[PDB]
RNA sequence: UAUAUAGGCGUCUGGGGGGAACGCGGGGAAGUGAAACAUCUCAGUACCCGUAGGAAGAGAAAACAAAAUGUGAUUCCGUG
RNA sequence: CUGCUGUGAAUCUGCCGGGACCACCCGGUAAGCCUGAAUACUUCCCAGUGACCGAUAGCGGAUUAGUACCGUGAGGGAAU
RNA sequence: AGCGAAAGCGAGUCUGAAUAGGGCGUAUCCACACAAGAGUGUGUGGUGUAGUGGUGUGUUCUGGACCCGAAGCGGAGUGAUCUACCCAUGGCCAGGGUGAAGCGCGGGUAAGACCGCGUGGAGGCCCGAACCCACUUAGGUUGAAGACUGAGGGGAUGAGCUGUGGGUAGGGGUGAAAGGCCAAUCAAACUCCGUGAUAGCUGGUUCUCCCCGAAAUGCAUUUAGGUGCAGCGUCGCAUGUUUCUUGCCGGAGGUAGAGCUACUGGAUGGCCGAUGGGCCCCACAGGGUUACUGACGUCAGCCAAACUCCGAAUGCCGGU
RNA sequence: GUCAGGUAGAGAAUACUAAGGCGUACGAGUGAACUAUGGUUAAGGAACUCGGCAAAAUGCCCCCGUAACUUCGGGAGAAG
RNA sequence: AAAACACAGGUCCGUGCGAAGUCGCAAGACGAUGUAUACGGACUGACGCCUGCCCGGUGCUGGAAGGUUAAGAGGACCCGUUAACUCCCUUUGGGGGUGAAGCGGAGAAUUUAAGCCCCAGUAAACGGCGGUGGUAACUAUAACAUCCUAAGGUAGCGAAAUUCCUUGUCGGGUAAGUUCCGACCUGCACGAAUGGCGUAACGACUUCUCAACUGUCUCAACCAUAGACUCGGCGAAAUUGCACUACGAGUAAAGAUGCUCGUUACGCGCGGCAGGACGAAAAGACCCCGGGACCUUCACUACAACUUGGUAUUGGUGCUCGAUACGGUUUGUGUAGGAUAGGUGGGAGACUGUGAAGCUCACACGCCAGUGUGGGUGGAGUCGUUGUUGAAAUACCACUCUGAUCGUAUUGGGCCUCUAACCUCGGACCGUAUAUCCGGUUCAGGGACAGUGCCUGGUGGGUAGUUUAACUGGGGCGGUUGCCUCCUAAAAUGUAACGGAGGCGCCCAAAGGUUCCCUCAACCUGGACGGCAAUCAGGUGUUGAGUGUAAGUGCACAAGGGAGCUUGACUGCGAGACGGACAUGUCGAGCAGGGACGAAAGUCGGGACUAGUGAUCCGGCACCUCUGAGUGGAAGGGGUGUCGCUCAACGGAUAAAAGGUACCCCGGGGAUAACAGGCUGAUCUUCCCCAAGAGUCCAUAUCGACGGGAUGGUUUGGCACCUCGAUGUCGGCUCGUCGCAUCCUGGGGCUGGAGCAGGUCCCAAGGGUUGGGCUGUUCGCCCAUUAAAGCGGCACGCG
């Protein structure tokens, strides 16, 4: 009487039970074809468990999907440019750049070692013990970088900007990830931890865009993340830059903000 | 409804109810005892029902018995 | 031995019983019926008797006694 | 006449292979022998064996069984004249407010909506007597009354109140549901009967004197405030000092005390001095120096219900 | 269950009355405490107490005028 | 009298109609003279916005391929009895073996329903709704990776009729705010029809506030009436061992009118007060014990009800399959070969023109190697012990297993039917003037079903009877219950407690018997691994090692270590004893049989010893010379050996059993708890001894650490001494009374006392010692005062 998600994770189909739920969610893994009727299934281990046959499953976290979705809309070159990750410590975003042939990447954490052992062996992988959260060091990360990916959680991503515009070059290219129910004053999270309010997302994206513009970093374009938090955390990836023909800083910022939520998700 | 029956009309002869105990045939507890209790007991008791008679019921072997050339319908009493 | 249900024979070199059953022996003759005496009792009547009571006893009732009275009622129930 | 489970045998019998031990039985005593002192046996004689039926007393068994006492259980009946609900057929509800729909008029509306005005008489409507309740409080509390009285209190045309007649009955009825009510009683009414229910529980049990005279412990217990058997009382019979005391004699103990270099543990201070500690010359050889920690040992003083190299007094067993 | 005089009054309420009916079955005394039932109370006014319990207070008619809120009926006899 | 019930509104489930449901044994009735917009049941409870997740558990509903399962059909196989033989062995018998039929007993395979397992749906069904590892804005305000599930609280609300902590925090309100209001979220232990959150109107509901009003109060005074009181009349009651019934300090069953010692008191009444008479009342209702009673449930065991199947009532024809008896085709690879050699008895002689041979196909199989039947053709034969071939015809009559077959006789399983039993609360007509009864007749429908008997399996708190241990410093909760060893245990034996420590419910065919032989542990010295340590050698070493297994007593004489043989880990017994309420239990020399070891002496009836166990009943099994319901057998019983009980509550109430009662009742108990009293005083409380210190120095102005000794009886306790045929339980009110351990007032000594004001100690009990807010409050917090707002005893004084 072994749980179906139990046998699945035992075989090696998915390294974690959260992924076992993702696979049963669309019914990618079942016996005799068909969607897995229910995640509560008593299946004998002598049966056959299938899979979506995802060829590009060389990923070790969920942060991969949201990134590959952003890079679909942006198509940003990585080789030949230094890169910065604002802290994932789980291989969600940096490992994708590894698959992108990144020249050299740097990642942060909360002062904790929990990365995949696979990434503890690549020479171009730098690990730091949360030197600082908001005012990132522009030189101790190895010098100048040419890309920064924003991945923040229970901290309103609006205080690391002075550091991330300094932790860059004069010709910089940045893709921040705006999480809606996390920009509102801490404690004022949306109803039940999930937000169904386009106007709240509008307020959050406007606040982050205006905070970026305060430094001069204008918003170029928008993107809706394809695979969000399971219970609900739909993200909206923007794009920071100070010198392009797409200097949407006066009126086009709002037009692009409507685009973000009108085509989101 | 034809055979007819169910019925209807008339004329007789009975039945009905009571009763203290005793009889016969049925139905049938619980308290109690078992130092608890259910089998078991109490007890086929108490009570109930149907029926009598001066008594009733039983009664003339499809019985006993045990190798005895033995008893011989039933009922009741004493023993065993 | 016996009730309800099912199945269900023979008429005497038959059938029943003799403490599972079988053989032999013995006893008897079911599925029809009547039957006195010896046995149980006393509402009532007669005549007696008591190392029985003697009026708080003996019947509840020696006297208005199943009365007066109590209870809606089944019923309880004096004292003299 | 007994032994045996029995067939059976019989002063024997059972077990057993056993004239080989034991069991039960051969009244009891006496003697004389023949065998062993491992508790005496065996045998020859003798003596010869006591029951039963009336009846008094004590105890006991079956019966209500020394007397009184439950809450309750069963059988058959009686009750809805109180109360619960229902059914038929009747009666009652002073007085005063409010002002629903409906209808009619006007305004307003493409037409409506709607409003203002009237008539109108709705309603588990309002205030409030009769009537029905019973919220507060005081009195009553061997009452006026086994549930009232006074002052206020809620409903008062309604799921209203009420009269007369009727129906539902006990593991049943009825319940706008409180285990409420069902005749001053209800977690199963009442009456009679079973019946003198049963109570390891409480209570009571009536004249005298004479002699003797306890126990409140052990064991078992659906047991722990009950009982059985033992102990301990009395009476009858048998035996006769067997009892008890004191002296002496023969014993076995491990308590008091003590001791511990006699063990097992604890435990005080010294003494020498390791091994393992550090350092020198300089190797991690080797050697010595040093608060070293300081095994073992040793000196002296100690401690113990489950320690004992020892070890009484008493008590106990026997003899005399 | 029926009948329902007068005067105030909306009234079958309440006060007093008519007709009619009663004075209903222990009394007579008496300025004790205390209890009960009524009454009044300077100044203060809930300080009482578990709590404004109980008392006190408002109370009728006619004009004027009425709030938040509302389910548009009400609240409302608001309050004044 | 309520917030509880009801309610209008909501949903869910059942019900197709003499419905379902209910009352009845039935008939019958209500439902309803209703018919799914109706009726019953369940929950919720106008209205408004909504009602999340979980179908794993348990129910409900549905389904069926399998597993399992009753009665009923089946009777293979076995056993009893004995007609017959067949034999001895002795002779007129009598035991051995076989044993047909018949009758009997136990009875297997096989077949068969529901249910259960199984798989689905269902939550406005009964029910459920998580964490961890390390984190940033200025700490936060749980929404980075991973474990687990049936899913991980949705919305809304939230110190709540819900919050112990708690008088949470902040604001309001008061002079003073434990209640209240508005919020906060750390929701011990809210949450979505046991609805969640709001809501106008309503309430003899609960709570907070303001105005007004007042004898509620400061703080009480006065008046009248009914009693009380006096006089006359009548005239009770509960109660009651007494009696010419003081107090104090004691003593006593521990709280005395009655006893002690002292003090006080002339005799008798009337009106008043309630301190005592553990006052009256009611065989304590709290608590324990015994017994009831009613209630609950997956306690036990039953029964109603519901339901399954078989069979009776109960029949007919058609098919489909199965079992029987009977008939005719039809079958057998083999090598020594004219052989696709069914097992045969007869076999010198059977088969043609009723057209066989050889040709045409099918039937039959085919390991397709080859052969039997028909007519269409066909022409007048083929065959044998032929010889090889175990077995010959494969030329013929009668018996025949293997098979592919049809039919008859018989009997089942099923299926579609028919009508004739039976059924209809469908119509009509009649008895019958009257009649929704009833019976009949007849038409129309079902129909061998249903219903009902009997047998049978399920479900079965719907009901019924009952059980649900004891010990216990009250009871409960915990723990324990039998056996063995030690200490307590006081030098015999025995000895209690919920006293102090541990073991047991086995193990070993050798770890049993015998015969013989040996001596360890530790220490020093010498040796490659090899270290203190492993095996070797030398020595010292009397017991410190080891003895299956706890502990104790033992054992070096060895009971300890080693080897040989071997089963005495025997059968018949047992003088005499230990221990003992009894029932149990324990030791035992010696005799005989038959053995083991030993030369023999001798030892051996398990183990160095003391745990390793369960009475009786009832039943099983093997053996025996017992019995055998007329007789012979048998069945059944009996003896002997043995088997089956965490009966572990271990002397074992049943084969079989849990809980609630605050709705409770009875019988008892001060044998036993709660209150008060009594004893004690661990704790509590109040003092003291010593003085390391602190105080700049200076123990002792003032505090005094570490330790030590006491008082009181106010606290929490310990005990269980009186009271359970009744000793009323907190706080406040009224009224006191006593102590002093003094709060104020009065008198002082020392000061680290200049004065003012204090600190500490000593003496002193005459008087005094406030009113409020918060709270049920005591306690306590606060407000305004005051000379001060003392602490205690008196049944935590006083109903
Ligand atoms: Mg008669
Ligand atoms: Mg009985
Ligand atoms: Mg009994
Ligand atoms: Mg009894
Ligand atoms: Mg006669
Ligand atoms: Mg006769
Ligand atoms: Mg006769
Ligand atoms: Mg008399
Ligand atoms: Mg006289
Ligand atoms: Mg009399
Ligand atoms: Mg009368
Ligand atoms: Mg005998
Ligand atoms: Mg024997
Ligand atoms: Mg003898
Ligand atoms: Mg005589
Ligand atoms: Mg005699
Ligand atoms: Mg009765
Ligand atoms: Mg009646
Ligand atoms: Mg009108
Ligand atoms: Mg109108
Ligand atoms: Mg009204
Ligand atoms: Mg009203
Ligand atoms: Mg009114
Ligand atoms: Mg009024
Ligand atoms: Mg009124
Ligand atoms: Mg009432
Ligand atoms: Mg009240
Ligand atoms: Mg009085
Ligand atoms: Mg009076
Ligand atoms: Mg009143
Ligand atoms: Mg009144
Ligand atoms: Mg009426
Ligand atoms: Mg009547
Ligand atoms: Mg009732
Ligand atoms: Mg009566
Ligand atoms: Mg009554
Ligand atoms: Mg009853
Ligand atoms: Mg009863
Ligand atoms: Mg009796
Ligand atoms: Mg009695
Ligand atoms: Mg004497
Ligand atoms: Mg005795
Ligand atoms: Mg005696
Ligand atoms: Mg002597
Ligand atoms: Mg001596
Ligand atoms: Mg000695
Ligand atoms: Mg000793
Ligand atoms: Mg000593
Ligand atoms: Mg020791
Ligand atoms: Mg000692
Ligand atoms: Mg008038
Ligand atoms: Mg009047
Ligand atoms: Mg007059
Ligand atoms: Mg006077
Ligand atoms: Mg007054
Ligand atoms: Mg005044
Ligand atoms: Mg005034
Ligand atoms: Mg006020
Ligand atoms: Mg106050
Ligand atoms: Mg106040
Ligand atoms: Mg006060
Ligand atoms: Mg009042
Ligand atoms: Mg008034
Ligand atoms: Mg107004
Ligand atoms: Mg208002
Ligand atoms: Mg007004
Ligand atoms: Mg009310
Ligand atoms: Mg009341
Ligand atoms: Mg209620
Ligand atoms: Mg409804
Ligand atoms: Mg439901
Ligand atoms: Mg029905
Ligand atoms: Mg429906
Ligand atoms: Mg409700
Ligand atoms: Mg609702
Ligand atoms: Mg729900
Ligand atoms: Mg669910
Ligand atoms: Mg579920
Ligand atoms: Mg389910
Ligand atoms: Mg399911
Ligand atoms: Mg089912
Ligand atoms: Mg059968
Ligand atoms: Mg809260
Ligand atoms: Mg509150
Ligand atoms: Mg709560
Ligand atoms: Mg609080
Ligand atoms: Mg506050
Ligand atoms: Mg609040
Ligand atoms: Mg519910
Ligand atoms: Mg709840
Ligand atoms: Mg719910
Ligand atoms: Mg509600
Ligand atoms: Mg609320
Ligand atoms: Mg409200
Ligand atoms: Mg009301
Ligand atoms: Mg009320
Ligand atoms: Mg005064
Ligand atoms: Mg007077
Ligand atoms: Mg007088
Ligand atoms: Mg005194
Ligand atoms: Mg005293
Ligand atoms: Mg005295
Ligand atoms: Mg005297
Ligand atoms: Mg007096
Ligand atoms: Mg008095
Ligand atoms: Mg008085
Ligand atoms: Mg009393
Ligand atoms: Mg009592
Ligand atoms: Mg009890
Ligand atoms: Mg049938
Ligand atoms: Mg049937
Ligand atoms: Mg049941
Ligand atoms: Mg029951
Ligand atoms: Mg009984
Ligand atoms: Mg008991
Ligand atoms: Mg007990
Ligand atoms: Mg205790
Ligand atoms: Mg105690
Ligand atoms: Mg001793
Ligand atoms: Mg001694
Ligand atoms: Mg003792
Ligand atoms: Mg143990
Ligand atoms: Mg040995
Ligand atoms: Mg041996
Ligand atoms: Mg050696
Ligand atoms: Mg040995
Ligand atoms: Mg043995
Ligand atoms: Mg003996
Ligand atoms: Mg021998
Ligand atoms: Mg021997
Ligand atoms: Mg027995
Ligand atoms: Mg016989
Ligand atoms: Mg015989
Ligand atoms: Mg036998
Ligand atoms: Mg026991
Ligand atoms: Mg026992
Ligand atoms: Mg038993
Ligand atoms: Mg209740
Ligand atoms: Mg009682
Ligand atoms: Mg006592
Ligand atoms: Mg007291
Ligand atoms: Mg006490
Ligand atoms: Mg006392
Ligand atoms: Mg100083
Ligand atoms: Mg005692
Ligand atoms: Mg006493
Ligand atoms: Mg008491
Ligand atoms: Mg008394
Ligand atoms: Mg009293
Ligand atoms: Mg008394
Ligand atoms: Mg006082
Ligand atoms: Mg003093
Ligand atoms: Mg003082
Ligand atoms: Mg002074
Ligand atoms: Mg001074
Ligand atoms: Mg003076
Ligand atoms: Mg308060
Ligand atoms: Mg005082
Ligand atoms: Mg007190
Ligand atoms: Mg006091
Ligand atoms: Mg009191
Ligand atoms: Mg009182």
Image: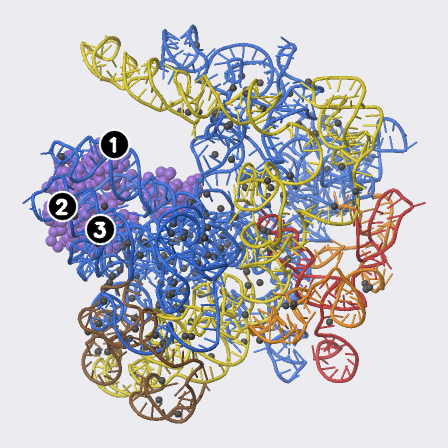
Chain colours: A purple, B red, C orange, D yellow, E brown, F blue
What label sits on residue A178 in the rendered view? none
Please tell me if label 2 and label 3 are on a single chain.
Answer: yes
* Separation of residues labelled 1 and 2 (CA atoms): 33 Å
Q: Position of residue F553 (x, y in %)?
A: 50, 22
Picture layout, residue A159 above or below residue F86: below
Q: Give x and y (percent) for residue A142.
A: 15, 34
The residue that mark 2 highlights is A241
Comparing E67 with D259, the one in front is: D259
Q: Which picture quadrant has residue A62?
A: top left
The numbered mark 3 sits on a residue in which chain?
A: A
Rendered position, F477 above or below F509: below
Pick whichever, E78 or F331, lies toward us: E78
Q: Left or right: E2 with respect to C73?
A: left
Distance Cα–Cα, label 2 vs label 3: 31 Å
Q: Residue F444: horizontal and vertical position, in percent? A: 61, 72
- The numbered disc on residue A187 is 3
How crowded pointer 2 is (Cα within 10 Å; few <14, some 14-19, many 20+) is rated as: many
**Residue occupied by mark 1:** A121
- Nearer to us: label 2 or label 3: 3
Q: Earlier in the sequence, mark 2 or mark 3?
A: 3
């Amino acid at each position: 009487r072994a749980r179906v998600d139990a046998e699945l994770v035992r075989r090696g189909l998915a390294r974690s039970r959260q992924q076992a739920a993702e696979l049963i969610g669309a019914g990618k893994v079942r016996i005799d074809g068909l969607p897995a009727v229910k995640p509560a299934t008593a299946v004998s281990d002598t049966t056959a468990l299938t899979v979506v046959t995802d060829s590009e499953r060389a990923w070790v976290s969920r942060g991969a999907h949201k990134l590959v979705g952003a890079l679909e809309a942006f198509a940003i070159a990585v080789a030949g440019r230094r890169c910065l990750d604002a802290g994932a410590s789980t291989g969600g975003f940096t490992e994708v750049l590894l698959d992108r042939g990144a020249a050299h990447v740097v990642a942060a954490d909360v002062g904790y070692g929990q990365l995949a052992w696979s990434l503890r062996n690549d020479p171009r992988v730098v690990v730091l013990e949360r030197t600082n959260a908001r005012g990132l060091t522009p030189e101790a990360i190895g010098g100048r970088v040419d890309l920064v990916v924003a991945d923040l959680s229970f901290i309103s991503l609006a205080t690391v900007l002075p550091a991330l515009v300094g932790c860059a070059s004069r010709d910089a290219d940045i893709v921040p990830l705006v999480k809606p129910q996390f920009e509102v004053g801490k404690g004022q999270v949306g109803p039940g931890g999930v937000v169904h309010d386009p106007q709240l997302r509008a307020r959050s994206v406007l606040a982050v865009a205006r905070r970026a513009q305060e430094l001069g970093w204008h918003s170029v374009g928008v993107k809706a993340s394809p695979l969000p938090g399971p219970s609900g955390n739909v993200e909206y990836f923007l794009w920071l830059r100070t010198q392009t023909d797409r200097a949407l800083s006066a009126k086009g910022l709002e037009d692009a903000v409507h685009r973000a939520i009108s085509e989101g998700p």
